Amino acid sequence: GPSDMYVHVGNLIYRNLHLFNSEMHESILVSYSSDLIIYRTNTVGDDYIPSCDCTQATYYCKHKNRYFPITVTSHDWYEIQESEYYPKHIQYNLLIGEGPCEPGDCGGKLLCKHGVIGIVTAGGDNHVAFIDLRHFHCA
Ligand SMILES: [Zn+2]
């Protein structure tokens, strides 16, 4: 659903590594540099990760409990200021754009007209960053 804070495609669940990492040894894929973890699940999800290059997007902002349109820009990597879960660091495979973000917002879905392309991973001042999931799926 629109409010689910993760992506569920077939039997794969995509989530923020910093909010998983507990059963990390049971996961199927981990990208430490991208705050991403993927694992097998027993139910089938209906999300779909496309392989487009869209920048016209929309995302779920948990603390506002609503969706916001957003224009995102790709970044192979980018500096990310310290937080409550990650200290100052460079993160990779990002999508950034302007919009609200507060602690607890990670996992929120970012979608383009084709499907889900990311999940919230970080928030700065007036900007929000997402993991570009298109980079972890075969076309
Ligand atoms: Zn698209």
Image (tube, rainbow, N blue to C red):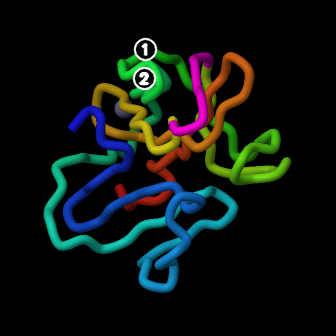
Can you tell which of label 2 and label 1 is closer to the viewer?
1
Q: Does the residue labelled 2 lie within 8 Å of ligand 1?
A: no
- For mark 2, give the secondary structure: strand
What are the residue bounds of the magenta stretch?
A: 98-104
- When the figure is inspected, residue 29 is found, relative to residue 124, above or below; the finding is below
Which residue is more in the foreground, 81 or 30? Answer: 81
Q: Are marks 2 and 1 in contact (CB under 8 Å)?
A: yes
Q: Taking 68 as reference, is 91 left or right? A: right
Identity, as a three-letter code, of the amino acid under mark 2: Ala
Tell whether position 101 is magenta: yes
**x, y (%) of residue 68?**
42, 15
Vertical relation: 127 (above or below) 136: above
Q: In this view, does 111 lie to the left or right of 129?
A: left
Separation of residues labelled 2 and 1 (CA atoms)? 6 Å
Could you tell me which residue is drawn at 33 percent across and 61 percent down? 13
> Quadrant location of the N terminus?
top left
79 or 93: nearer the viewer: 79
**Where on the image, by quarter, is ligand 1?**
top left
Image quarter (top left, top right, bottom left or bottom right) of the C terminus:
bottom left
Q: Name the residue under label 2.
A: 57
- Residue 138 drawn at (x, y percent): 38, 61
Pointer 1: what residue? 69
Query: In x, y percent, where is residue 52?
Result: 40, 38
Which amino acid type is shown beneath numbered disc 1? Pro
Q: Residue 3: percent from the left, percent from the top? A: 29, 34
- Residue 88: image tag: none
What is the residue that sits farthest to the bottom in this orientation? 25
Q: Where 83 falls versus 12 (above or below)?
A: above
Q: In this view, does 77 lie to the left or right of 16?
A: right
